[PDB]
Length: 147
Length: 153
Ligand SMILES: CCCC[C@@H](O)C(N)=O
Ligand SMILES: CCCC[C@@H](O)C(N)=O
Image (cartoon, rainbow over all chains, first blue to last red; front, side):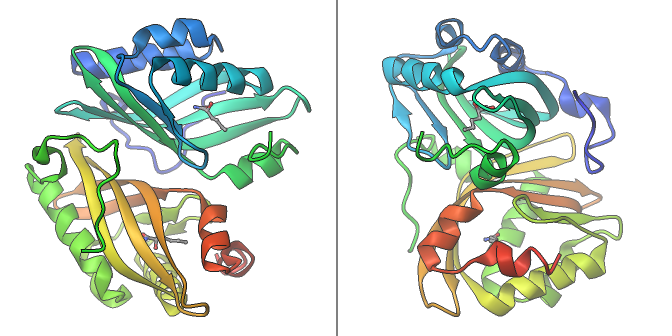
């Protein structure tokens, strides 16, 4: 379900990994469609954090794993479409769509996300995704801020 | 300033500094936002351009981009821009930042957490997209902006 948005950089290189950190993050993006917190957590450092910016952050591998496990109980990531990826000293940015399905309603939405990852020695010390939560809630008829 | 570092920001100070010509242009642009002046800001844009605050509709072309910025500035003021992380590759610049925004109708302020992307060619902006949660911002400054600036777009 990976349609280009109109504004995407036309060079296909803009969406491809050209550094070891970009390569790890693209592999991580590939893994997201497993909807499997236990597989995902292997990419993370000990001193780490995760935040979907409209919701509270999680600090440390255990809390990150439990947050993801809880997300996957109410929604599934059916596809991940990465348009732009860039890296520089320890940070990787991804502009993407995650096609998300709300399990209670069966409804899907193409969630526009800009995400940032911090790495050290090939492991994720931070992951933050920025998007508009209300629009997703209304598309899939489900209030997530409560949950 | 009004610039507090989040807990999670990369500790090396290099992470928030420009080290490419594209990064430097984008930081100058970020410095200009506190002008609250759409006519000044439009100078940084290419002809084939676009702007989008991602919870609202995109604007295509310089006049629409200028009108969108002008519309925002009729009702809010950017009091400060705090850039934590800046990176560029491949004609793209990314900025992780907080904009301290004050809603003019209510007088209330909010530290809006933003991740934005810029596309550039020959030193001009061909695309600018800012990602953030609009509802949190509306509820903080007691202003339904989507209701207002949604129809506007
Ligand atoms: C609350 C929406 C969460 C979205 C997130 O799981 C993703 N990266 O798609
Ligand atoms: C609708 C909120 C827009 C936020 C934006 O003006 C910004 N600070 O760049």
